[PDB]
Image (cartoon, rainbow, N blue to C red):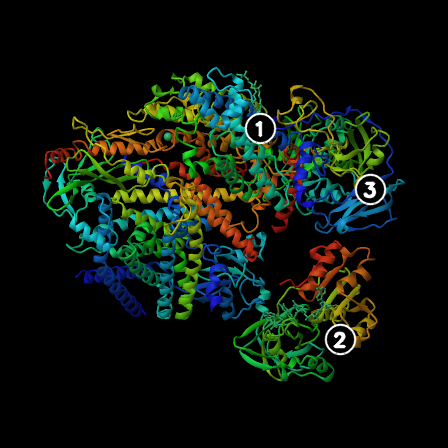
Amino acid sequence: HEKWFALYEAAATLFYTPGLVTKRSSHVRDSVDLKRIMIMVWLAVFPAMFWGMYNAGGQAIAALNHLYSGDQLAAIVAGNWHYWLTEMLGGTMSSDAGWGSKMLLGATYFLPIYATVFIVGGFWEVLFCMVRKHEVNEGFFVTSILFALIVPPTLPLWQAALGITFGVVVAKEVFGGTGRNFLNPALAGRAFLFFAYPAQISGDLVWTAADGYSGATALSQWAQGGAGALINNATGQTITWMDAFIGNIPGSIGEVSTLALMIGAAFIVYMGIASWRIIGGVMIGMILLSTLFNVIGSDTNAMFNMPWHWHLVLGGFAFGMFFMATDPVSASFTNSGKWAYGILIGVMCVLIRVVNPAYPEGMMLAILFANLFAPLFDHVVVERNIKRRLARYGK
Amino acid sequence: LKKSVLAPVLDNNPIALQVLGVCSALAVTTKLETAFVMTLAVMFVTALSNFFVSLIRNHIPNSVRIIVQMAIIASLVIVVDQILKAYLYDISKQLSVFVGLIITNCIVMGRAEAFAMKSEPIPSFIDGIGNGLGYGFVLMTVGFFRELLGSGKLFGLEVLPLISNGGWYQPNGLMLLAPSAFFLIGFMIWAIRTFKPEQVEA
Amino acid sequence: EHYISLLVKSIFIENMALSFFLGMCTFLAVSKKVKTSFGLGIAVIVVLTISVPVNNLVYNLVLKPDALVEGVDLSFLNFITFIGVIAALVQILEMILDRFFPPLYNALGIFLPLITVNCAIFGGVSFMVQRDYSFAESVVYGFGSGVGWMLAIVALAGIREKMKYSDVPPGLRGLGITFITAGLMALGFMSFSGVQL
Amino acid sequence: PHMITIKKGLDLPIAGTPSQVISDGKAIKKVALLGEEYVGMRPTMHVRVGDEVKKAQILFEDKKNPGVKFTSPVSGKVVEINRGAKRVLQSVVIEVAGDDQVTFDKFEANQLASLNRDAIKTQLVESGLWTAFRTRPFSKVPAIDSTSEAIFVTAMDTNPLAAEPTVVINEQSEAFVAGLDVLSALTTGKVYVCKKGTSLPRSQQPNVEEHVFDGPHPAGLAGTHMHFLYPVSADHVAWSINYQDVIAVGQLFLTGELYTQRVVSLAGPVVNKPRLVRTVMGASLEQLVDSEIMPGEVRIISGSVLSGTKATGPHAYLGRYHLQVSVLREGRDKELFGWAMPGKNKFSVTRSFLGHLFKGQVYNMTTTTNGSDRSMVPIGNYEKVMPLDMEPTLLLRDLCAGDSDSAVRLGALELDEEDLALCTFVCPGKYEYGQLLRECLDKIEKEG
Amino acid sequence: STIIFGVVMFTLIILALVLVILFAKSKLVPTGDITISINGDPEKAIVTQPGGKLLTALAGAGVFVSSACGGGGSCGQCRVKIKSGGGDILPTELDHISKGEAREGERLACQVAVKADMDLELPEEIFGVKKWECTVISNDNKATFIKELKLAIPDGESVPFRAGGYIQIEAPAHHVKYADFDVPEKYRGDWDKFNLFRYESKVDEPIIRAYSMANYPEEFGIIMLNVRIATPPPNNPNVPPGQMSSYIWSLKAGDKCTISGPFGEFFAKDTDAEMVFIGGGAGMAPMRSHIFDQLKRLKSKRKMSYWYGARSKREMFYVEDFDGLAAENDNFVWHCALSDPQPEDNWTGYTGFIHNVLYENYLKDHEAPEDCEYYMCGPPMMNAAVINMLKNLGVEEENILLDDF
Amino acid sequence: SIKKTLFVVIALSLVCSIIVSAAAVGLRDKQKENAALDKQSKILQVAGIEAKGSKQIVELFNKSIEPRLVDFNTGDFVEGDAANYDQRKAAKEASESIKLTAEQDKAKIQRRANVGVVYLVKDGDKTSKVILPVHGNGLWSMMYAFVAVETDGNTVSGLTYYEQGETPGLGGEVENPAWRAQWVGKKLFDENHKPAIKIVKGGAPQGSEHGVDGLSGATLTSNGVQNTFDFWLGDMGFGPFLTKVRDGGLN
Ligand SMILES: Cc1cc2nc3c(=O)[nH]c(=O)nc-3n(C[C@H](O)[C@H](O)[C@H](O)COP(=O)(O)OP(=O)(O)OC[C@H]3O[C@@H](n4cnc5c(N)ncnc54)[C@H](O)[C@@H]3O)c2cc1C
Ligand SMILES: CCCCCCCCCCCCCCCCCC(=O)OC[C@H](COP(=O)(O)OCCN)OC(=O)CCCCCCCCCCCCCCCCC
Ligand SMILES: NC(=O)C1=CN([C@@H]2O[C@H](COP(=O)(O)OP(=O)(O)OC[C@H]3O[C@@H](n4cnc5c(N)ncnc54)[C@H](O)[C@@H]3O)[C@@H](O)[C@H]2O)C=CC1
Ligand code: NA
Ligand code: NA
């Protein structure tokens, strides 16, 4: 029964810490390990996940009540299992629906995607580990949760499975696994979906989980017209900066609320898991490019007048900066490299947001570009260090 | 001679073991018909260039060997381009600049210099035919996968009904972009070297 | 201005190595070391900058339809004219460097034989002809395409150097993993597709 | 003097600190010389089991380093010659008995500074004190014919549970000054005495220069001192010696006899009365720590916990460059969801554990790895503990990948295994970077 | 028509390109002769046009260097300290030249290509390497598949040799048949057991090969040698026989054969440590050379052991000589082991693999094996086994002398 | 031996140039015919005449399709070689083209050719419709199409996009047969004779005369199509020609 030894070892180590002792120098070791690091990152996104489920349910219910009423709404509820299951479990689908019903609908829409991505990615990881006679790394939990939190609520399960398969096998496993790749696996899977099935991950019919509802998101609305165009058609109210900051807007499950993401990011940064230098660089680049665009101005491209705070609260900027750009493996391994990496991420994200009409948001593409170019930053820093060493550090 | 001419297909692939003729493999592989026409053109050009170089291998001055070989290759490619414009105009338009880039294709020049220069005309012709056959095998595999999974079609014939035409299959847009060819070639090399471990690099 | 936009487009938006798969053989062969990749990129930059304008001048003077003489178009000599011009330029540059500038030949002249008939130069010239460019426009386009190719090769070299710590399965080690890395790089570079600069 | 402050490092707050008071200590009947602690040392034996040896008598020579003699710290009968796998000399053990000893020339305290370099080298080699010197790069015993223009005297000890060098040196100030004078005569360049702020006996020679180093543990390492004062490379080689060996050199050149007495801090979480004790070089630790450790399964370590040798079996003897005995508990226990519980009584460089909230806490650290072996994920722990001007993440990745050329370019030649001990401690992947560095240095030396 | 204009333009473009290339070559490429300096000696200098290899240039000049593999960067014995010039070091060269040696300036002569002025320093010992035309003396079979051949220099500048060295011999195109081989009845029975005479060789290309010597220094103007016929492997007899081996076996008394000068560094250290010799088959030649040099020319008192591994009794030679030497001096002890003795052998002594028997008999009870100098020479597999055994016994590479090549 | 090298190179160049020039000159006519027939097939397809095979395509195009040149500024027919005309080259040339201001350039096309080419579908001594080539910038590339307009000048018989580079599935649906067929019967201009064709998001009202369902999830391409039609139905486009045709310009 040695074939399933990897799975048995993974389960045993998950339940109990191993009793291994040191064998060489440094007979004492730090208490922190990959398990704790990955679990801390995984828990840091729990507030974002819960608010995302709540917001998805609330937006879906509002759109449903804005589009249908009475027997037509009942027919829609009966036609959708996401709706009649919520009704069955005590969650009303009416306008006077509580936070509990909204969270239940969000769960019905999110948990299937999370389960599918987790199962498929874990199967691929286990297959690779068993075939190559390795142990199971702990980063898959973070990869799966982050992938599940950056997709529209209405994503097909087969599409989610294909995306996670690509992100896990093509970007990580073929490179040896966790800690041995250069690209972000979750963002690689999301980009695979982006460029393979755009119709399901873009437009106006995917960011709100309501049947027959068409509504643009904040970035698209700002692109069309400008700041005055930000209106929530479901409720007919202007989208305020406070609304976007708290996360009461359509979009991906885990991206909407900047406040919850800020809380989780603050916790992980205080614990030292996430590099604050990368976050600072991202903020510096975003602010600089946004201010430059505002100063230059434009009479045709409304995005040119988007303030830095609006850039911060709109789209998946906060989620990317806090959890996707801080991936230690895909970032620079030097402090100066981290600064340059963050600055490049921010600049590229703002540039794709503004001067690229095809894509309303560009945080994922910017992070992929920065992942490609980070080794060059660390190489430049290392070459400077080597020159200093050859100079005997000025001695 | 069958083994000698079939060796380039798998034993010594121009794209899977040698790094040659990758531009056309990555670009033209969008459609199976274009891949097939490119395969035929490369086979013909390589075979004819090898044959002529072997015919006048002894009389070629060394100081202008590269120019003499490139002149023959360019003349053959120009003739092929004119032929593809006269017939198969749509395929020629789809191929675009890569028909002309066949001249700079590494396979043709490498075979001409390594084999045709110091080999008899008929063996050089056979070597060119085999190298083109292997290049075409790689191109055909990649293009078949790309076209099938990106359009539900083979040689323009529907094989998978698309949803847009009242079908059941949603085409994979990424199969019509650059990364698809890269990934397909990488995994094809993986499979080839898994079935032939002797080619595994260190 | 127009030239700045053209340079930016030819560097980022129009990237030869990944967008058009031009020069991929040397791209995947010489990307092992960052210094070697930088030298090869500089060589490609200089060769493209010295070839595209000469090819533009030759095309305008002779190969253009009806330019040389009324009712006569020699567009069927495009390929041989361009490839021969490039072959002559690369060889003469490699020889003059080896003669007068030994350090320059050692730094860059080593790679010129690989650029003599490289696909990147021919593809750039072919795209320039298929488009409409002046002499200055051709110079800027050649320089920008060379810079973009250098950027792509240097990024690939950096990634490959970083991958010294990776554990690639046998059979995928080397050419296959390089191909997968190039595909991921193309994915990352697709960010500029929608820009119409 | 000239003060250099280190901001990046880690002072391990391990429980059981020494009392910093010198005690008589137990009686040692077995004294051993460990053959595996000398880098690149292939021994040609000069004694056999049952042979009678005097103090400062050669037991074996070095094939790879001709002229280097390893002498007996004590006079008595050779009882064991322990050879491990591939007949690697694990240790040569001598039962102590008698007073017979070898003697050498002696000089007045006012002549040592003017002694000839050749005479000093001859006396040191004959007495065996030459092996006290270690060459950076490669941390090997210097060649007899070789010379260096920088001798680093480590008069400070920042290792956890380490004795205070000031207390030891105050007893032997005259010997320390004599050793400093001898080192000043021997060195072609300068003698950098690296110390803490507290005063120490001072030599009058212009060559000897006192340098004060402040900060956490890495401040006390000869590697850090070399990096900050005399950067080393293939073309520039420095020598390293500790204050106890300097006292021994001074005693040798003052009295004509080898000085083998040492003061070692016996301290640890499982030590009833941690304190400094007098002992002899190569003393048997099973007898040194006898009737002084709490019951249970424990590990005795010669050297600090960060960098030391597990004193078990043939290696159960005090090392040549170790001035400390650390006794720790064996952490073989398994607990349910231990990696998830709040970090009360858990120490970490990161703030992921509750322990860091309670300042001044002391942890009864064990030998547990606190996790399985995983790939290296650079969360930034190495930079927090590496003070040297280097890229620790990239250097450690090169060491893991076995890229000797890149490691040398990144500064692997200025490092010893003790320099990467904190990196090993803080690594979440549980890499032992000392072994990787030693392998890289061995490959570099063999190739060059 | 446009055909004429197109043809004219094509011809003009091609002619312009060719003329530009020719003019660039004429005005940039230097055609001057390249000068190679040896030890900075004007008398010992070479002039040659660019091209070829440095080894070929040196051979044409007259100075010879070890070419055991005959080029291709395999043996690596060709080593020249190029102080300046010669270009960088190739990856194939790096396979045998370490980083320290490369920094010192060592390069492979057969791999380095001469194109410009280069200065290299070569030890004066190389000037002692000369090419001679020796005469055959005896070609009597000495075993079933091992023969002793004695080539004598015609008193022409016979440079003294060193024990343990080897020479290099070139055989031009020729044709030989196994029938011409000389085999007394004792070995001819085994030879005809499988009708090994059915084989024949036809060399269509001169071949250069390096063979060890078998004569101690006290022997003047004599080059003894041992040759093992490279018979086709029993598993695949269809493969052709050994070119050089068959040619040497087909030689006749009085025939003139070309030989090169002394080569190799397989010399004994000038110490007093115990010596252990591990020979087998053709290794008997160098082992005998070393033993006779140490016991006759020097008459050293060091303890010496010689373990020889023969496939069968019929493969044992020089037994009487070694027994007489051991009787004369007890400091030398010999012990031969038969790995695969035939039933007719009736051997009663040591059997099995030489390394295993040596380890079980002597090294197991030896107090300080690391202090013993182990010289060995035999098949590659035997060398690997002995090296592995010695390493397991903690013997360093310095004390182990082997012809790695 | 420089003479031998010169002889061999010049002889090889002579033979290669002879064969290359022979092939090129021989195949020039066939290549021109192939390109012409490729254009003719699409023109006939938009006209609504079924044609299979090169011979049938040529015969039907010669019988029915009548090319003509129209000056945009005046809207009157202009004499010239309509069949062998390249409006793209004419637009590229500054002398034969006009630069457009930002307000004028609704379709984001830099230059407008002074003289365009239209095709009259002759039913026999009578025109049944006029096919106009329009084009405008899309999200990724420039999209070209043929619009067939009845003799009244206010009805769309058919539309086809014969050159586009939009993303398949999202932006490529302009080539969808259903989307193209939906265009039949629409009114280019309203009662006031102004651009009235509209692309409406989320479908169009049933029975609408000027509303066309947009491209799902492709609002940018739909906007490009809207801008193309708005420009090419205005004064700077075929507005004057269509106005003339409405009053019996063709008949
Ligand atoms: C420094 C030095 C010293 C040496 N000293 C001696 C010495 O003292 N005595 C001595 O005998 N040798 C000595 N050698 C070895 C010698 O140089 C030759 O390598 C050896 O004698 C074989 O010569 P050959 O002509 O048979 O070689 P080759 O022609 O290279 O090999 C012939 C052998 O290869 C087999 N073979 C070839 N191809 C195949 C195939 N496809 N399948 C199966 N079998 C195949 C043939 O059947 C035959 O057995 C020495 C070598 C060196 C470098
Ligand atoms: C596809 C197959 C099925 C799987 C998909 C998911 C659906 C099934 C499982 C859902 C889990 C919850 C089970 C049902 C709870 C029902 C609770 C209840 O009493 O009813 C709803 C109630 C709110 O009621 P109220 O708003 O007052 O309205 C009542 C009438 N109007 O509710 C409340 O008071 C609030 C209860 C909210 C519960 C849903 C949110 C759960 C989110 C946590 C999931 C996290 C798991 C992943 C993370 C990692 C886990 C290790
Ligand atoms: N470099 C030099 O100067 C010389 C090199 N040689 C090498 O030695 C070879 C000897 O060949 P033959 O005479 O045919 O040898 P052989 O067939 O007579 O065998 C000689 C010995 O090798 C031993 N042996 C073989 N395989 C072994 C294994 N796997 N493990 C342990 N012992 C093993 C046998 O037991 C025997 O004792 C030459 O062909 C050449 O390669 C020989 C003489 C000089
Ligand atoms: Na938000
Ligand atoms: Na955008």
Is D237 located above or below residue E378 in the figure?
A: above
Q: Are marks 1 and 3 in contact (CB under 8 Å)?
A: no
The residue type indicated by label 3 comes to Thr
The residue type indicated by label 2 comes to Tyr
Of the 4 image quadrants, the one containing the N terminus of chain E is: bottom left
Instruction: State the mark number for residue F211.
Output: none
Q: Mark 2 or mark 3, which is nearer to you?
A: 2
C19 left or right of E222 in image: left
Q: CA distance from mark 2 to mark 1?
A: 79 Å
E137 left or right of F174 in image: right
Q: Position of residue D21 (x, y in %)?
A: 79, 24
Assign a secondary structure to mark 2: loop
- Comparing E362 with F125, the one in front is F125
The residue type indicated by label 1 comes to Trp
Quadrant of ligand 4 in image: top left
Instruction: State the mark number for residue A42.
Output: 1
Q: Quadrant of residue D128?
A: top right
Instruction: State the mark number for residue D103.
Output: 3
Q: CA distance from mark 2 to mark 3?
A: 56 Å
Residue ID for mark 2: E318
The chain to which mark 3 is attached is D
Q: Position of residue F227 (x, y in %)?
A: 25, 32
- Comparing A49 with E315, the one in front is A49
Is A104 located above or below residue F137 in the figure?
A: above
Instruction: Tell which residue pokes out farthest to the right in this image.
Output: D98
